[PDB]
Image (cartoon, rainbow, N blue to C red):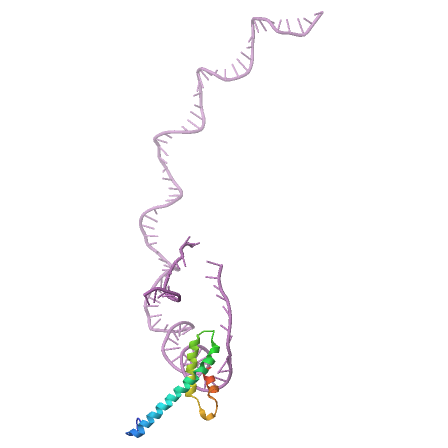
Length: 88
DNA sequence: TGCATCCGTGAGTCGGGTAATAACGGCCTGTACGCGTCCGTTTCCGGCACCCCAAATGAACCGTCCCTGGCTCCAAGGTGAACTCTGGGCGACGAGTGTT
């Protein structure tokens, strides 16, 4: 929003925003690397037909990306239950 | 600095075809198909303006392809006689033969 129709942002008001942006992206990454184990545990079951183990794993990884992007913590549910549907 | 440890080529010649998984509503659209209507086309019914067109209806008609007329000038049918066989008619002569 500040890019066009903004203000000459001072350093105190710019560096903090940049830092929190990087922090959020890093936290997202961290959750993904945490839950790849759930991804592989789910994808182990669909083997033996069509495509290979690693292809299934990477498709589950894409599904996990989608699940994290569309997750909602306010609902007070464990993340695994929501992510399983998207992985599948 | 060997040294095991893979590691990369053989090794010839002309009956067919064999299987798995949670997935389920709900919205969009898109290309193909299915309705109703209108207009160019086109194609013929019968009309001329007449275009005339013509095979069919009167002549001659003249050469010619048929009739009738007379005339021969001859070669075939009718009129002879003989004759050389053609055939019958006449006659004599001779042995194989009916008989006591």
